Length: 171
Ligand SMILES: O=C(c1ccco1)N1CCN(C(=O)C2CC2)CC1
Image 1 (cartoon, protein in one colour):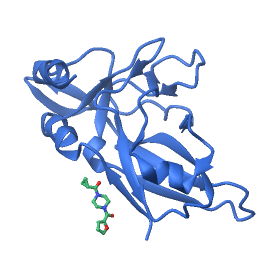
Image 2 (image 1 turned 135 degrees about the vertical axis):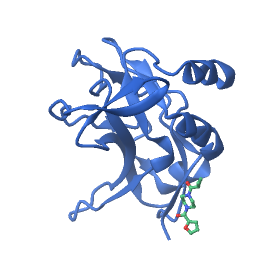
Image 3 (image 1 turned 90 degrees about the vertical axis):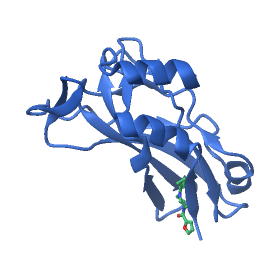
């Protein structure tokens, strides 16, 4: 059976309990924690590409008020479709399953200024989603897993000083 497990789930849950934040910048900022998954039940012989996108979680934006995240108004129009191709793509099942798949180089941005970046709306909540695309498949089979532990609010600057401190502690 195909199984995609979140790595460092305990670390992600430490951030999620505070409400996770990821910085977005003009030039793009790498994530901490880094999304990493373990994979079993691929065809070791088949070739696959790994894609990453970010799904908008809510029909509203968020605001940090009195040390609490609360609904902060109507959402901006959805960020454009941005898919990140894992740089090991395409590769054998055996490649993806032999060691955890790390999305260490993906950059989150609030400006479409190129460079394979992911455009996100500040003060909106997103949930990372990984797609496994089988290569040379006339049916273009794709599997999609969501990672609820990895939900975060995109921010131009950290709102919660406990998040700022956590990011420094574990990174
Ligand atoms: O789908 C399965 C699974 C396990 C047994 C039968 O199916 N898993 C395990 C739980 N997962 C995690 O990411 C763990 C929290 C870290 C996702 C993958």
